[PDB]
Length: 132
Image 1: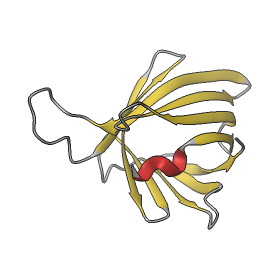
Image 2: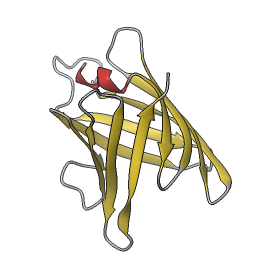
Image 3: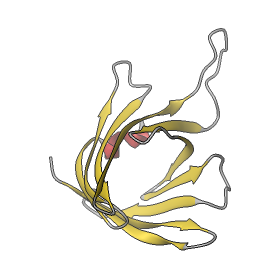
Image 4: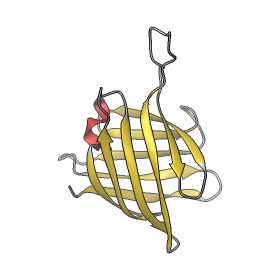
């Protein structure tokens, strides 16, 4: 429920250009992100479902909040979300991965600015601005 901050429509700049939306799913266990982006001029879209995984017949959900991102090009990417105060961390695959997004919400919760980190290209800056 701490990911409620993400609910809304955001313009995205840096690494990609466009807009994304987060809506909570009924029951409040999963966030649905809709992605409408451009990268190198080409359209890049998909969805991502954010929440803990829980096996039917388990008492407790998973320890990690998780997501799977399904994109227009046919790839699937798995993340782990951590929100610790105003800092969001999105890990590729598992907490502590060499590739991750880290960003901080502005004091008004309307701007989330940070950067992707990974070996090779190093990463790149990204900012989201709440727009609706």
